[PDB]
Amino acid sequence: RLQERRGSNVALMLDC
Amino acid sequence: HMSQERPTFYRQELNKTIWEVPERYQNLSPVGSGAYGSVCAAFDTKTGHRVAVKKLSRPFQSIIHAKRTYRELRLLKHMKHENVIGLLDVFTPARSLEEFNDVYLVTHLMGADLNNIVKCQKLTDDHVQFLIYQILRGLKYIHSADIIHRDLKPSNLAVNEDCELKILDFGLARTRWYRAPEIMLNWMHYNQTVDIWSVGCIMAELLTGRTLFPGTDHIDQLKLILRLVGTPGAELLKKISSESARNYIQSLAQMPKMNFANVFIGANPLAVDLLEKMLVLDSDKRITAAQALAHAYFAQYHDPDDEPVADPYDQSFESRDLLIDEWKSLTYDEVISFVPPPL
Image (cartoon, chains in turn orange, brown):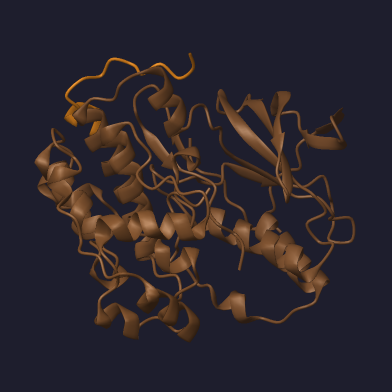
């Protein structure tokens, strides 16, 4: 139920 | 009796040593060697996930190693929480106690740590709320079992692309930038609020983009800390066991606690308020994980019905005085009694 609570659900980038 | 069917194992030499793992684990790739063990990333064909597989280096060479191996296995088998490292699998090629020499632990793969996330984007206040929320949710769980992590820092926090976080790499011994002052200089016994100090150091840095206390040795580190939180008051001095440490502290020019709002202008004031409550010099007066979860900073994420506590964790084994082969046998029993997670 934590992902529903988030303001935004655009994926973070993990390596760059 | 009702022991798991033994998988088919295969052997490969990766770098220094022979790895013998179930065929379930494929495409093993070295991810680096620590002092106590060697770690490969692997594809777990049973779950479809990439995992970390740690081979312990000669875990039963000594009492210290044998007990340390037992300690780690007991701890990973206990911890069952979305925000904490869990034991996915533990295996040995050994068919008996007599041939048991090697222990492999399978745990959540470190896809990215909190530093990798900071490296590749600017976190929003929402990212910071959710990241710190999950750390505190994990800590509520471990602290409720009287487990102390002892070494919280960004490199021990795994984060996926959904900004989901797990606490990894617990301290198993019986950079200092994130360490509570009372343990950095051995002023008194570890209490679980050493972890809260660490969360405060991490949150400050995620808010500002700057390490809070990037000291170069213990003295420089302690002076940076005391410059922000003030020199110890008489009440804290009573609780410091060493006369030498007490004498040293009394030698310091008394300093006032700083106003945090002036160190963190433009940060969410509820974040700064929570930071104030985490970075209190007196470990007895720091907010606990459970209290911290109720702070208004986390209003969006807080759910008192989904912030679970742990089963009590029996650590009486810590005071047992046993032979190498007795620690080894206990470890073997814990391998045997291992029940994999569902699904």
